[PDB]
Every structure is written in structure tokens, then in C-alpha cells.
Image 1 (spheres, each protein chain N blue to C red):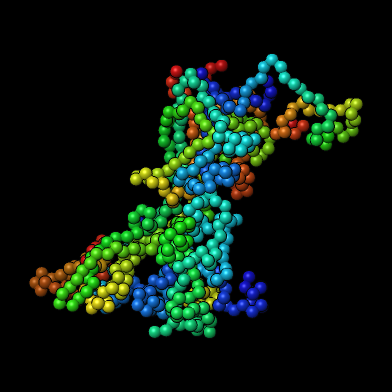
Image 2: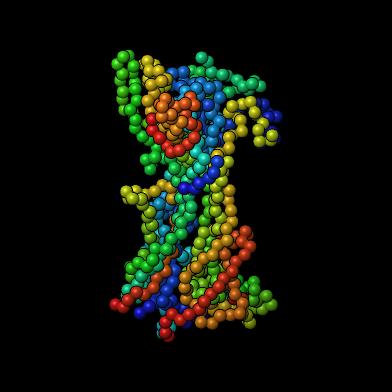
Length: 54
Length: 180
Length: 82
Length: 270
């Protein structure tokens, strides 16, 4: 009986989606300099408060 | 679960700040620092208008209290109209002949931050400006003014036999403000 | 108040009654000093809206135009059950 | 500015048009002759003031020097702060049984028709003697001079040690770290009791202003603050980041010493 909650946040259950996309703007510059579309790296974190390295 | 998120327990902080950039433009156009609106939501994904409908919820199975600390700063001058330190009333002589006539007036000082001696000079100056606008042109002399603010102890050099101030001048030392 | 140790304002130099008063050897002037205050703990509402009103008034319940900085900080905690 | 432009294009040293003063003009004014009888304005300091000629003005939209002058707006959240000659109605400085029309070195005092008032206007005269409901007094306010120019708050951040307070987002951008405490930037005013800066000694309008009997200077005082108890992360890394930012969330280059001391303790179970 001691929790503190903010109305814009809520936890997740039972199912969701993960996206694997080959043309994110930040991933192009810092991850895939020597790669091509047949073998590449991508970030599944969709939060722009962080760089792909972070 | 996502590793950058975690829930909160037992205590936190809420900030009430008067100079947020977005709140200035859209909330407080007709307000001042004595009575204003502010947002306690510190998340810039939303405008203050959008934030107004959001809430922060403390668990309803407990009763909560809040410890409050404040910081305040002012710039008030000591002689001003809002605090009634600007004016006073007095009764002076308006006409000589001998028949003498008197009347009440209200006197006004200009605003500023002054020492006590400088304030007393301004009160004397207000009396005299009344004697130059009325008075003087109606036959009163500069020996019947009738209201003065002083600081001296008259009768200091008094003599018990002759009952006069022997030096011929009153002692020119300040003791306490006085009305003559 | 602060203490220190030390002609339109003299129109009747000759007159012993109307001479300009002597100045005190102690002079006082008024100062504004920032105030930091702890007000203790007060009961809090269970649901807090995102926009809040802050007000400062005098003894006659007028707002004061000479305030130019005011901040508040609140620290919630549990007082009792239910 | 008048020596680099201006002077070489025909302007005289009697049409400058902007001056900052401290005097109360019209002190020795006479209600019958309507002139300053002593022949010189009273040389005493009352409050900082702005004196203007027609066509001139000052603008404090991007400046904090209006706080040092003690002139503020009654609606401080409305953007823009400009004071022009047309806004100072009723504040004309009385001239000089005839007014003096020129100075010792033959400089015009800009006396007008009716031979009582001068073209110069001042904020202080308009505030105190002008129309209460139409002059400058209706939307400006007179305050004590603040030598620090107005101090604001500072914020502390410890992103690797404390949990984020409610509604703050986790991030690695410096201008958006969650805030763990607040206080005033520790600069304060102190009071005391008491020629390139005088280029027109003869001119009664352009003379160097008298100095106040009260002088104020700003000081830096070390600040020792207790911020209370905040929730702590269960695992603490060996290297920690410490940040101090201002109200606009910029770092402050004038901090040269900052220390923190933390005392952990148990708050609740599980």
C-alpha cells in the first residue's frame, strides 16, 4: 500500500510486437557501414532517448 | 519488462516552479509571481495543456502527507503606495487677516527606498510645498507654518534661575524623532 | 532593518526653530533577504492533477506585487493506513 | 556610439537622447512661476531613472539590466519590454522671470514654447506625477534595485545513484536528466553606507548622476544544503555522474566546488 503511479505509464501483459527494420536512420550511420541488406544489424529498442550504441 | 523502466515506492519529490518555458507562454499571460499556474508533470512529450488532464496517484489504501519547503525573494521599497507608507494628514493655516483660518489636507511623498532621516526631510518638504501654493499668497508669514518634524531635545541647556536657554542656540544633537 | 554608524532641504538656515534637523549617529535602512522555510508535514490529496495553482497573500488577503521569485518542494510519505 | 556615428553626421552634444540618471527633477518647483527656482536641479539620489528625447527609446526584451534599475512590468509573463518617448506622457522635466535657454558652453537645453517645460521626459516623473490611469504607472512597477540582476534556482542530478522521481523519463541527454534537488544559486546582495565618466560638467541635464548613500554589491557565499531522503538503486556502479544545471537546463561554468554525501538506510520490506 505504498506505490506511486503516473497516469501515462502502464505495464504490459500476454503479447506485443517486435520490429526488425533495415533502414532506421541512426542505425545506418553507426552500425552498418560495411554491411548490405542480406546481412545487417538493427535495434529492436524503439525509444529515441538513446543512441543505438547505448 | 523493459530494463529502462521501474515502478516507484515510499517517497518521491514534486517541484512547483514559476519559470518553466512552456508554462510562461500558454498559462500565465495575465498573472504575476504572487499568483500563477504551473505544471507538476516534468515530461516534455506533452504540452502543458495536454498535461492538465493527467494525474499522479498515491495508493488509496494509505493516507499520505507532504513535507513542504519554500523559497521566496522580494524587492519591496520602504516608501510606497500599496502599503500605505506614502501619505499622512495634517491641519495647517490657510489665511491670516487678525482672524486665522485652518484646514485639513492630505500630503503625498514620492516612492523609493529611503533612510529614516531622508524620509523626515521629505515630510517637511511636503508641508512647505503647501505653504507655497496656498498660504503665502493669502498673507501667512514664514513664521506661522505650524507643523515641523524634528529630532532635537529642546530645553537641554536650560537654567533653573533665568529659565532661558543660556547658550542662545538649542543643542544641535539628535535624540528621537519629534513633532512640533 | 540594518544599522550603520556615521539647499531645498534647508530653506530657513537662520531660524533656530526651522533649521534642518541634525542627523542621528545611527542610521537604519531596510533590506530584502531571501527566505528559506520549512513548514512541516500536511495531509495530501490522493489524486493530484497535472496543473497546480500557487498563491501568496498578505494579512488583508491581497496578493503582493513585490514578490518576484517563489518555489515549492514537496516530499510525500505515508502517514497511516486506510 | 555618438563619437563613432552621429557626431560626424551633424548631431550636436545637445540631442543625445538617452541617459540613465538618479535624480528627482522638479524637487524645487514653484507653483506660481512653474520653474525650478534655485536654478539647479537638486543633486540627491532617489531611484534609478530613464531620460528620453523625442524619437528615442530603450528595449529590455533580451536583457536582465531592468532588474538592476528597479523597473519591472506588472504583467511579467507577457513577452516584450519597450519604453518609448510616447509612453512617458506627463513626465516633462521643468525648465530652469524667464527660463534659461542655454548652458555655460552654449549648449541648448531644448526649451519649448510656453517657456516652462523642456523636451526631456523621465520615467520617474511620469510614474509619480503623471496620470495614474493612463501614464507609465498603469503597467510598470517601481522596486528596489537588485545588484545581482535576479538570481534563479539550480538543479542537482545523480542519474546512476537515485531512482527517477515521478513523471521524469529515463534518458542520456544532459539537458533532460531527472532532477533530485533544488536550491537558489548562492549569490547575494550586501549593503554599505557611504574624467571619462563626466564629459559635460556644465550641463545640468548631462551632469554625472549623484551616488546613493546606500551602495550594494554582490557576493558568493558557500551553500550547505540538506535535501532529505530519496529512494536508492539496489546496485550501484563504481563510477558515478554528477551534474548541476540552471533553470534553462544549461550547465553553469561558475561552479568550482561541488561535493555530495549520501547516507543509506532501509525504508521498507520487499
